[PDB]
Length: 190
Image 1 (cartoon, rainbow, N blue to C red):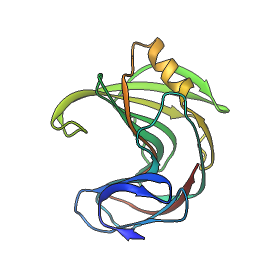
Image 2: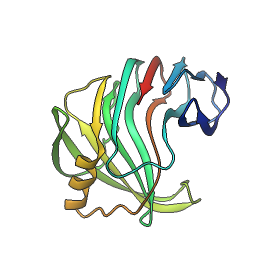
Image 3: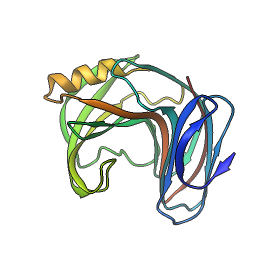
């Protein structure tokens, strides 16, 4: 069903939907691992389905339609605690590469494409444990796609060889983010 921001479990899967209150976004939980997002001149939002808690070796499958009209990205997104880390494995994006401004650490090959690895620090930003300071890790896919399989272990291992030691995994979802743009997406996670 179409819901206001929140989290929970729907049809077997954890979901998380958040927006900045701007308006212009409609998030709908669908059958099984499916979710749909339709936005028009939105603000900033992030929504998707997955697991809570996630794991360090989950192989995530996703398929569907991703039609961004401007600034937006499709990614595996999650958090870790001890250390507190917010991470993204970006599979596709619209007009803006979300890793812009981040520091490149290296590259990793996974699931048919090379990914560029980045990191950036966030000071006194909102997090799953409140206002805190933490790193953001990014794996950005060179060959964009809207369907496929992501072997998370390849990314966590690569990040570990670059100094990132993940601790306790919190949620882990396939999410669609929009940033003051328009678009539509219908993604199914499994």
